[PDB]
Image (cartoon, rainbow, N blue to C red):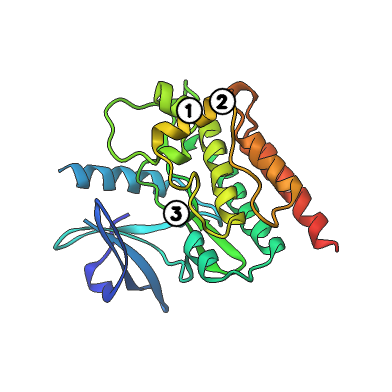
Amino acid sequence: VYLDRKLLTLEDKELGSGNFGTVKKGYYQMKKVVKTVAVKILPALKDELLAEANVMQQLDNPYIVRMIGICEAESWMLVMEMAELGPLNKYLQQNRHVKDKNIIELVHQVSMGMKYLEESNFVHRDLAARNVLLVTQHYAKISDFGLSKALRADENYYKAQTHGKWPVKWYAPECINYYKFSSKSDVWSFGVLMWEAFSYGQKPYRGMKGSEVTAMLEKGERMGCPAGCPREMYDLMNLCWTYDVENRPGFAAVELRLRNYYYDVVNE
């Protein structure tokens, strides 16, 4: 779990920043190879990182950004796999000629990763296009496990109490109203992610306040079909946005719907 500071080199390339601190590009020397890595650099911040680290350690799947380990130096450091092409929302913004089949491919990969997380009884709680990272144009991984929670053995939801930065436009009604987060809450977020992807990285609920989204959703209103989005994918989107948790699909069924449609488009 713990890494060697002598084997780690930090570059000048800042990849991103948040409240926690920054993420920087780095290099970690292995047995024979040197591995390009992304490094999260930071009492409250340290305990969150150690929690994030323990969450990430349990997780092993091709469609998630894996943790290499942790390092304590000038600051606490979380060393993770590098996804060079960056966040999906920004990529699609800068690459408008990306094909419909390609978007389906990428969102299907996210659903496989989320299917695994669901199976593992972890809730992501920050599932958005900005947090899905591209290794290649045809290979996406889920990242940013800062708000993620391992579910208790006897519970299918996590109940929050005190809170700060919450991405409301991605949050299900049960999250906003009851502070309750399940894998079905991530499915709602997945629907918004799908909308983002087929909108080529446009922000959801443009120009709207959190409260204005809530009123919209209580009217039974949902975001419309993005231009060029296939009807089968918009229908899956809306099903993800089922108000009632009990009737909202799980990720297994979502992944299956995406898997089936992708192969149908592959045969064209």
Q: CA distance from mark 1 to mark 3?
A: 26 Å
Please report contact status of discs 1 and 2: CB closer than 8 Å, yes or no.
yes
Residue 14 is situated, as x and y percent measured from the top left of the image, at 29, 70
Number of the front mark, 2 or 3 = 2
Residue 180 at least partly seen: no
Frontmost residue, 241 versus 27: 241
Residue 235 is situated, as x and y percent measured from the top left of the image, at 71, 40
Relative to 94, 194 lies left or right: right
Frontmost residue, 191 versus 119: 191
Q: Residue at x 51, y 56 (%)?
A: 202
| Residue type at the position of mark 2 | Lys
Q: Which residue is mark 1?
A: 215
Q: Which residue is mark 3?
A: 131
User: Which secondary structure lies at badge 2?
Assistant: loop
Among the 4 quarters of the image, the one containing residue 136: bottom right
> How many residues crowd mark 1 within 10 Å: few (<14), some (14–19), many (20+)?
few
> How many residues crowd mark 2 within 10 Å: few (<14), some (14–19), many (20+)?
few
Q: Earlier in the sequence, mark 1 or mark 3?
A: 3
Q: CA distance from mark 2 to mark 3?
A: 29 Å
Please report contact status of discs 2 and 3: CB closer than 8 Å, yes or no.
no
Quarter of the image with the N terminus is bottom left
Q: CA distance from mark 1 to mark 2?
A: 6 Å
Q: Which residue is mark 2?
A: 219
Residue 132 is situated, as x and y percent measured from the top left of the image, at 49, 56
| Residue type at the position of mark 3 | Asn
